[PDB]
Image 1 (tube, one colour):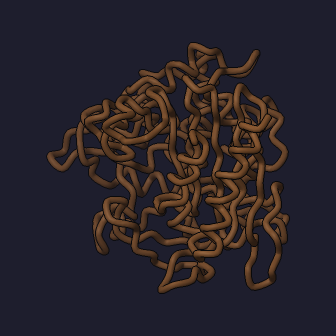
Image 2: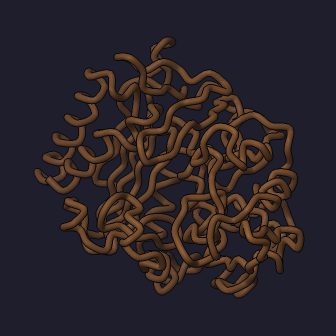
Length: 381
C-alpha cells in the first residue's frame, strides 16, 4: 500500500529527527492494524559509545511496561476464577493489613490494586525523608538486599493515603499484585509470568532478568544538551507532576537474585510487548475472552483523575481515554495507553483497530517528551 509506506515516511521522519536533535539515542517502534505489523523499525544505537546499532530484537528495561504484563496474568487468573476482582489482599497476604493515619485498617480489593485506588504510593512520588524513604521501601528499579516479601512487609507498615477505592494514586499496587499472584498459583512470580503469560502468548524474550548482556539496550537519560548513560543508583528529577526523584540501577536487569518487581522490574523486546497489546485490544482464543479485554478498558477510574492529563481515566493495565477532544489526541475514546520511565509508550485504539509500541533507551524523552506524541501523530497522519 502507498498509505503503509506513507506512514513509514512520517514515523521514520519523527525518529530520525529525534536522533539528530539528540532527544533519543535509539528506539524500536512497531505498528499493527487488525493484528498485522504494518510498520517495524529499529533506529539509532543500543549503545552510542560502542556504536552498536539498535536492532528490532534489542531487549529493554521495561519499568512500568511491567504492569500490563502482570495485570494480564491476574485477569487470566480471574477468568479461571482462581482470583476475584473483590478478593481482599489480606485474604492472600494475611500480613498485608496497612492502616490510614487514624489507625483504621480498611480492606483492599484486587480491583483497587489493578486501578491504583488501593491508597498505596511510590517512594519516587514522595519527597526526600518522606515516609517510604524512612521505611526503606523499594520501588523495584534500584539495588537492594530484599526479597519481594521483605519489601511488601515494609510497605505494610506505611500509612495508606486514602480509603481503598476513593481515588487514583500511581502506586506499588502491581508489586503487591505480583505477590498475590504467587499465593494464587503456589510458585514465585517469574514462574507465574512464564506459565500464565509468556508460554500462552508464545513470547520469545521477556522476563525479570536477562543473562544476554550484549543485547540489552544501554539506558540513557536527558542532560544539558546530549543524553549520558545512567549510572547504578543515580537519583534523577522526574518531570513536573510525575513525582520528585527516582533511583535507577541499570545493573538490576542482570541480577538473577533481584526481587521480581511486577510494577517495574521486567525486561523484554518490542515484539513481545506488541503481542501483549494486541491481546489486550481483542482477546485471543483460549487466552483472554473479548469480554475481559472490554472490562480492562472500562473507566474503572473516571477521567476526573487526568491520568495522562485531561480526558484520561484508568482501567486494568493502563489509562482509558474518555474524551479525545479534551485530551487533544487523534486517538479515539476507549484507547488504552501507558508507558515506562526508562523511555516507553504503548496504546491500542479499539475503534481504529491499531496497536503502537514505542520502546526507547532514553528517559524521560521516550516516556513524557515530545517523541511518544509525535509518533502518535505520525500513526494517525
